[PDB]
Amino acid sequence: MASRILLNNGAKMPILGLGTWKSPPGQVTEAVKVAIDVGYRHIDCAHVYQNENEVGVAIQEKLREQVVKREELFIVSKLWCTYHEKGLVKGACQKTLSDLKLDYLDLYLIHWPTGFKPGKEFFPLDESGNVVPSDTNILDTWAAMEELVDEGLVKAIGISNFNHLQVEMILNKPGLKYKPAVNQIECHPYLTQEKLIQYCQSKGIVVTAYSPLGSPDRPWAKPEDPSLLEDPRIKAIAAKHNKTTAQVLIRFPMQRNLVVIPKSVTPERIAENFKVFDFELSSQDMTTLLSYNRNWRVCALLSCTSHKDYPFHEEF
Ligand SMILES: NC(=O)c1ccc[n+]([C@@H]2O[C@H](COP(=O)([O-])OP(=O)(O)OC[C@H]3O[C@@H](n4cnc5c(N)ncnc54)[C@H](OP(=O)(O)O)[C@@H]3O)[C@@H](O)[C@H]2O)c1
Ligand SMILES: O=C(O)CCCc1nc(-c2cccc([N+](=O)[O-])c2)no1
């Protein structure tokens, strides 16, 4: 299987990347250094993760060390919800660029369709804990994203956690200048996303699967929660192919023509997780994994469920 997928901006995106949500700032520099050493060329970042400076130290050292060239790296970051106003988007991008010590991003995503009130708080709340929305709408934010392409700050723009109606809204935006290149969404055998993925692919939008391992370190994990890594049915498929469960869970989206971004700060796992290009799941394996769907989401916050733009009321 090829290692990159062609985007609708003409650039190629590595289909395996390293996630960095929850990667501790004191561990993620070494994690990214190790990742590049063992072959990763795509790093998934975000301002809200509060570790972009430390990710950048790693990227810069490996560029200076001549382990890799910048053109060979695919660095993604995301515009946080409190910066959807037109006048705040460039600054938000430039802070990400300064922290990552880059002069462009390969891909910048609108992190969520929901805009929040600007200010220092990433999740501004009212007295009863509802997030405070902003009045910006997604189409003006999108035009601000298009400006970043035209200023050379980013090579591609896209979206994340957009539902099909929301993707459609961007695609039908009056005066649309650049189509989203990517929609990054939660996707794994308990949330298989067939409808949203086929819609996006039919429009030439590449889908990135996040939390492919079910995010076992998410802060709100509950006993009763399903566990991909521990699911005996998936362990069995892994056993059959002489791979680990995680390797199965990473290969699965790759064979759906998705990009996948498993997170780890554990060197042995970082290496393990990249060793997924030398085996194939069968069609039957794939259909079996798809059958485990239960519409289970890692990422869906109660505090945002009344925002007008909350993406997960619609089926997809
Ligand atoms: N667009 C958005 O809204 C959004 C939302 C969620 C996630 N994402 C992106 O997606 C990335 C991946 O999602 P995620 O961080 O939620 O979780 P994930 O990649 O599904 O799972 C990460 C967890 O799995 C562990 N793990 C990694 N490799 C393993 C292996 N081979 N064997 C056993 N355990 C392993 C990691 O542990 P150690 O780190 O301790 O090894 C960590 O606890 C994020 O980091 C972020 O970059 C984007
Ligand atoms: O940004 C990441 O990579 C994941 C951080 C964890 C996470 N964020 C959210 C979150 C943030 C903003 C909006 C929503 N919403 O449901 O409308 C959910 N739910 O879960």
Image (spheres, rainbow, N blue to C red):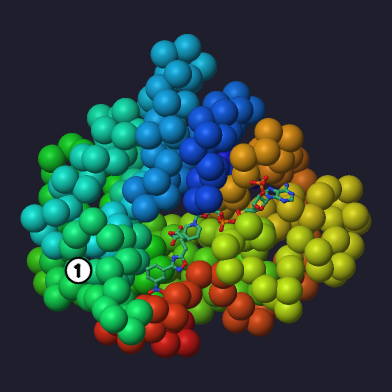
24, 158: nearer the viewer = 24
Q: Toward the viewer: 199 or 253?
A: 253
Residue at horizontal 74 percent and vertical 68 percent from the top: 227
**Residue placed at 53% from the left, 60% from the top?**
209
Which one is in front, 242 or 81? Answer: 81
Secondary element under disc 1, as helix, strand or loop, is loop
Residue designated by label 1 = 117
Q: Is residue 117 left or right of residue 293?
A: left
In the image, farthest residue toward the top? 65
Residue found at x 68% / y 70%: 189
Q: Position of residue 141 (x, y in %)?
A: 18, 63
- Tell me, yes or no, if residue 123 can be seen here: yes
Q: Amino acid at mark 1?
A: Lys
Query: Residue 183, how many percent across, how many down?
Result: 40, 62
Compared to residue 2, the image places residue 36 above or below, namely above
Image-based side of 202 in relation to 90, left or right: right
